[PDB]
Image (cartoon, rainbow, N blue to C red):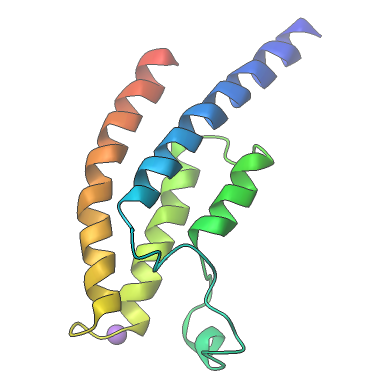
Length: 121
Ligand code: NA
């Protein structure tokens, strides 16, 4: 149906916008601390601590499958990246601190993304 086509075009356009958001967030992580999953071969005890691991490569895989139906879903995944890091790592670490700076810088990007999603529909 044409109504189904129109819904698919909207999901595609949201995907486009979320790709640009993902690229902008990731630029805020030049150290690439959050680029890839924590390897269970190098923090063997990770999944005892963190129930829902998340990273930018995992988000990009979901995005390329048009797996985010709205901005809230995408934000949930970004908050997991930050929040998981702030639990596993102590305050005094480069990891905890990098997560704080990513959250702060990413707030800016996400604020305008919400306005654009709402405005374009
Ligand atoms: Na902690």
